[PDB]
Image (cartoon, rainbow, N blue to C red):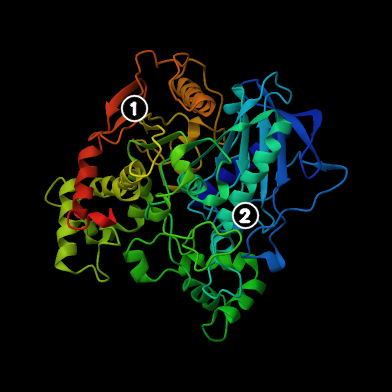
């Protein structure tokens, strides 16, 4: 990231700190938890609303020392009053703006927000799980501010969880107790806390909604797939992701050694000696080197992250993913809660930055063999059957004689997002009680209000609704400003937060009390639908057939001779 966006972000970071002190009140308050009393503070928003803020509530023991790479344990309760008027640190990660490592291994906290501690009725509880490919992200208010949601009468909860290798190291040897998915086991434990403690903040423990974007969506989906969370919540919203996306799981048991070797380990490849090294390595060294773990072959086969959710090699007490996600959908309790899913209208536009550095990637669409789903493709991607699959993909996105960047970014939309959504809906249909799933499509374009992800994807002055463009309408962030209430941007905040809280409340996203929705007939998807219907969200709200459908059926036809793997 550029020297300009570094000094520019440095200034916004200094401004957000002064604004944050300014928007603080003196009204501290104490709430109960099952671990003891916690002290929050009331804060202000730039729209002159206010809310109660409880930050840095631990939901697990600090995962340092001998708990590193280990599943989380419950924290130690306290007497007295724990100070919760400040944020704790984020998980150790690479700062996308600077390139420097920041964060700390002491990162397992959640934040709670509400406009009213003592409501006259129990409120819907909303749990946001941030994305960031399981390697970046946080629950700080400079990125995920609760300002838009607290206009509504809900309880909003932002969780944190272990990222990267600290979150997802996985070793085969059953003796060392590092099955993997520690970061997801964090998410489970925080859900258990929210279940037992939301009532103390006015929430309804029997009306809990979990949602997230990107990696947060996959996390959300995993929380719906695993037995460990059964019955903990009641609604799910999957924004631009799920657990059968190709980027949302990996077998990384062999990559620990590679990581150890990059960090200066001397010795052989057995798990015990690898673990001992990594256990005493400085945290910021391991995080800094993750970028170098993936082999050139793995990058070629579109492996995106070296560490991440994985099928655990053996089963233990807190096991989360004992089988491949496709298999877990067949029994998932979460199939029987109300679900909303959606994408933006140009997901792949996120990859503009990557293309700017690697223009050679556009040539991959000459055959598209690299984008054939890995379970169908051959190792070298040279088999004639793989060249045949690649051709089907090619027909779907290359519009002219030579592939372009736009063709590329359009392909990505489907490879990483639309095709996975489709496979999930069809899988779920064969294994569900018949609870509704609602689709949306986010199509609202605006340069007048943005979020930090647009600095990373180099989305400065770029038309189209990229992946993460919608976060701007859910959360306040240090790049936001007060919008006139009649602006299209402001209306979209109102609509977006309106629909989400409405779905949270009733398991149905339709409300005639939301502006623009008077002609809307939002029907859920049926198994007998050949075509998907989605609420298209733009300047106007309109029900439509999903425009990506034809290309989705193209990708599906790759599995013509292999229908078992669909």
Q: Using the image as rendered, state which of residue 564 and residue 517 is in the foreground.
A: 564
Residue 23 image position (x, y, % from top left): 70, 29
The outermost residue toward the right is: 80
Question: Where 403 falls versus 379 (above or below)?
Answer: above
Residue 286 image position (x, y, % from top left): 58, 68
First reached walking from the N terminus: tag 1 or tag 2: 2
The outermost residue toward the bottom is: 267
Quarter of the image for residue 195 reads top right
Q: Using the image as rendered, state which of residue 285 and residue 508 is in the foreground.
A: 508
Quarter of the image for residue 130 reads top right
Q: In the figure, is residue 202 to the left or right of 165?
A: right
The outermost residue toward the left is: 401
The outermost residue toward the front is: 433
The residue to which callout 1 is attached is 536
Q: In the figure, is residue 489 to the left or right of 285?
A: left
Q: What is the total number of numbered labels drawn onto the structure image? A: 2
- Residue occupying the point 53% across, 78% down: 261
- Residue occupying the point 46% across, 62% down: 311
- Mark 2 closeness class: few <14, some 14–19, many ≥20 residues within 10 Å: many
Q: Secondary structure at mark 1?
A: strand
- Residue occupying the point 56% across, 28% down: 481
Question: Where 347 falls versus 168 (above or below)?
Answer: above
The residue to which callout 2 is attached is 91
Q: Using the image as rendered, state which of residue 446 and residue 518 is in the foreground.
A: 518
Q: In the figure, is residue 247 to the left or right of 498?
A: left
Which numbered marker is on residue 352?
none
What's the distance in space between the residues labelled 1 and 2, CA to CA? 35 Å
- Residue 281 visible from this viewpoint: no
Quarter of the image for residue 129 reads top right
Residue 148 image position (x, y, % from top left): 57, 27
Question: Where 175 falls versus 188 (above or below)?
Answer: below
Residue 267 image position (x, y, % from top left): 56, 86
């Amino acid at each position: 990231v550029s020297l300009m966006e570094k000094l520019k972000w440095k200034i916004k970071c200094i401004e957000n700190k002064f604004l944050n002190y300014r928007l603080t009140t003196n009204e501290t308050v104490v709430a109960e938890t099952e671990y003891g009393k916690v002290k929050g503070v009331k804060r202000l928003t730039v729209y002159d609303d206010s809310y109660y803020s409880f930050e840095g509530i631990p939901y697990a023991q600090p995962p340092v020392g001998e708990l590193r790479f280990k599943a989380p344990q419950r924290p130690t309760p306290w007497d007295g009053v724990r100070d919760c008027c400040n944020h704790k640190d984020k998980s150790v990660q690479v700062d996308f703006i600077t390139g420097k490592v920041c964060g700390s291994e002491d990162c397992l906290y959640l934040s709670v927000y509400t406009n009213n501690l003592n409501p006259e009725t129990k409120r819907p509880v909303l749990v946001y799980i941030h994305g960031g490919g399981f390697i970046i992200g946080e629950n700080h208010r400079d990125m995920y501010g609760p300002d838009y949601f607290i206009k509504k009468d809900v309880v909003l909860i932002n969780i944190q969880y272990r990222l990267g290798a600290l979150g997802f190291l996985s070793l085969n040897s059953e003796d060392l107790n590092v099955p993997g998915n520690a970061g997801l086991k964090d998410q489970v434990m925080a859900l258990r806390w929210i279940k037992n403690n939301c009532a103390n903040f006015g929430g309804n423990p029997d009306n809990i909604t979990v949602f997230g974007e990107s990696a947060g969506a996959a996390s959300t989906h995993y929380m719906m797939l695993t037995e460990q969370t059964r019955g903990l919540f009641h609604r799910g919203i999957l924004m631009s992701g799920n657990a059968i996306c190709p980027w949302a799981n990996t077998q990384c048991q062999h990559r620990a050694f590679t990581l150890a070797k990059l960090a200066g380990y001397k010795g052989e490849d057995n798990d015990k000696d690898v673990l001992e090294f990594l256990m005493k390595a400085k945290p910021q060294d391991l995080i800094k080197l993750e970028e170098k773990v993936l082999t050139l072959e793995e990058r070629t086969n579109k492996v995106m992250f070296p560490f991440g959710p994985t099928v655990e090699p053996y089963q233990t007490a807190d096991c989360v993913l004992p089988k491949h996600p496709r298999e877990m959908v067949k029994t998932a309790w979460g199939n029987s809660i109300p679900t909303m899913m959606g994408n933006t209208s140009y997901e792949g536009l996120f990859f503009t930055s990557i293309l700017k550095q690697m223009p050679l990637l556009v040539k991959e669409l000459e055959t598209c063999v690299n984008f054939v789903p890995s379970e169908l493709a051959d190792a070298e991607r040279t088999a004639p059957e793989t060249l045949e699959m690649g051709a089907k993909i090619k027909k779907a996105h290359v519009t002219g004689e030579t592939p372009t960047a736009d063709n590329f970014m359009d392909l990505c939309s489907h490879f990483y997002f639309w095709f996975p959504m489709h496979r999930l809906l069809q899988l779920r249909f064969n294994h569900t009680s018949g609870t509704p799933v609602y689709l949306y499509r986010f199509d609202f374009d605006s340069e007048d209000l943005i979020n930090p992800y647009r600095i990373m994807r180099s989305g400065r002055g770029v038309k189209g609704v990229s992946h993460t463009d919608e976060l701007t309408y859910f959360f306040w962030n240090q790049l936001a400003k007060r919008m006139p209430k009649e602006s299209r941007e402001y209306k979209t905040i109102e609509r977006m937060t309106g629909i989400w809280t409405q779905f949270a409340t009733t398991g149905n996203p339709y409300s005639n009390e939301i502006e623009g929705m008077e002609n809307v007939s939002w029907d859920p998807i049926e198994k007998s639908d050949e075509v998907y219907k989605c609420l298209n969200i733009s300047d106007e709200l309109k029900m439509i057939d999903v425009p990506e459908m034809g290309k989705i059926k193209q990708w599906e036809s790759m599995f013509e001779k292999h229908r078992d793997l669909f």
